[PDB]
Amino acid sequence: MKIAGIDEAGRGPVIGPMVIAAVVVDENSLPKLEELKVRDSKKLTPKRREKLFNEILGVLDDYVILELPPDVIGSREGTLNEFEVENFAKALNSLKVKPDVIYADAADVDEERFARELGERLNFEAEVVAKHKADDIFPVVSAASILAKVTRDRAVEKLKEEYGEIGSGYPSDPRTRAFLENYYREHGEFPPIVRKGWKTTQDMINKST
Image 1 (cartoon, rainbow, N blue to C red):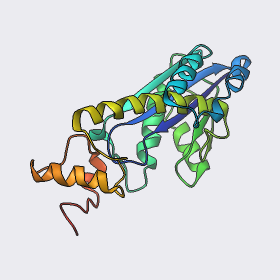
Image 2: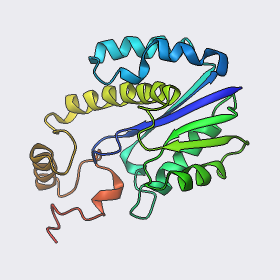
Image 3: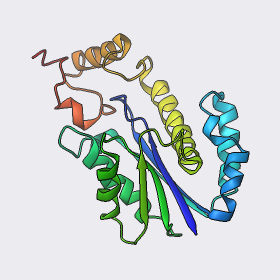
Image 4: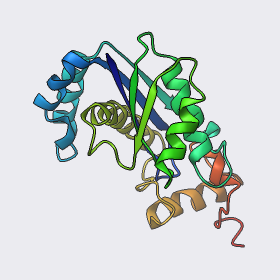
């Protein structure tokens, strides 16, 4: 069988793109992922993760990485379920090697619903197994988490070179609020890197509602 894993990176912050990676591995190659100890890579330095990233590509039958710019982030109703179900399926439907079983990270408190909704949006048939923070449970999902994290960290690093001190990207980060506030001050608008779903969603900065 062909097992696939899919996860995201950059869901919390409201600055920069969000990345969704989907990988596919033959069941007989699954072990190779654990031998690389992918599930325990969050502690690695960026360069060491960079190496792990390249190693992972060697065992996959196929994979897809989708870099979602902020201008398109916010296609849902409050709960970021619609946006992720829509894009997770998009990534999965883009694979050349169709998996039979797909393990997926579920942000929605109702894992079962997420798996079901995702499955009905596929252009192919496969069982879906969704779980909260699945990158710590399913090796295949962790592998995907890594391709996503590396891709996003590179994007962010690029953003810091262009705009400078942007903070962590969280609205609760004073440095990030300064960046946003100062930009709007000398531009009368928010920087293009701020996600659509927030600039209009309780953006309590220029609004101060």
